[PDB]
Image (cartoon, each protein chain N blue to C red):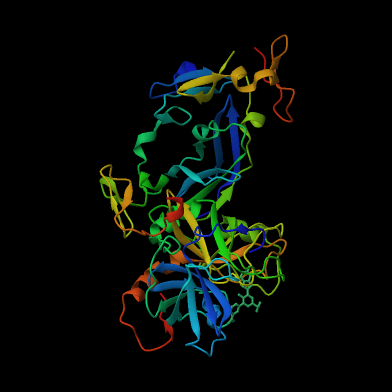
Length: 94
Length: 254
Length: 149
Ligand SMILES: Nc1ccc2[nH]c(-c3cc(CC(=O)O)cc(-c4cccc([N+](=O)[O-])c4)c3O)cc2n1
């Protein structure tokens, strides 16, 4: 258990009744602080971070897209409308 | 709509109201200036195919204000797999005669991209359904537009929680369920065709179409919607084809 | 694809892990967790593990009640859908960290603005001790006492 340092990626182990508790650092999670939070940037994982559409590519980063009437911005995730009455926006709450 | 509130005029801009001979038919959604989506059964008893109009901008059905826009419906296309009288493949694409003018009270709803629908919108818990349909299983229809916020369920949990029978269709892969089962909130007769809209990061997309599953606000039951995801392809394809020669059109599906 | 079964929450000082069965011969699992009224968030994407760590999510509001489900996909067609075009899944019991986590000042996996909170900063006057010492949260239904040192 802790003796047998099971916690990875900087984590600290706390012992219990044979069991232990790993306290990980902000970027990792898992029983043994082993999963890295920054390696699951896929479209199934919170839409890849894209505001509207996301695409996963083989061996290369996923790309975000926009709906007709909007343009992807500089950050590559957010879309902004290029029209006056872009779909799905409520003018009176704008 | 049972359990809903009144939609603050202008907050449901994609809501359509179809009329036949002047009488209310169904509701519908505006996806673009000449295209509206509604529920195929609403055209099960139409033999006055030119006396069909669509209104946008609408809110209070008793007074006219400066907003309602009306266009005749030039064409009605339904899956060639819908069966006159069922709830499966209950989707209709209506081609207006002339476009509408978007304004603060008339904007379309984004028809989302399948993948995004299936993978992201579908796990957004609450969406809105709206209409001027009965306010109680067999009560008065509304005059102001009413909107209901419902939770969606996956078929496994819907089936799991519904009471067992009535002469119900099955929840096919072309449907989904949303609602409460404690007969408190639900879509209702008169709301048919209207929208089920999900709000994802700032925009609303059309995730469903109010079908007719459950008389209206029953107990041990949920409301059934048409799963639009299964039809984006189809709609899109139809929206880019030449006008073809028919008011009712039954397009091949898929 | 068989669905997962025996979904269990294993939680001590808020470190919350869900575990389940079976151990997957040619299928993968993905876990989703939500609150009664929240959207579902996915974790442990397409794994072959039978445990998922949700601490990150439940420590956000330890007083909410979470519900989770595990989906099973064959491996390869991890798009897999069944008759009603959705992926095979099973749900877990509800877990309300604050009322069902296990106990052992102590640090918890609960974090506030980057730091970790402690047993008392999390249970205020609902935490009492005994003398050998045991930790007791009398305002509980289950897991009201800890163990002893
Ligand atoms: N929760 C809901 C939501 C929408 C609903 N719509 C209906 C509905 C019920 C009937 C009467 C019946 O049960 O046969 C008729 C229609 C209806 C509406 C418009 C057009 C036609 N049609 O066949 O030309 C039928 C309904 O939408 C029930 C219902 N329930």
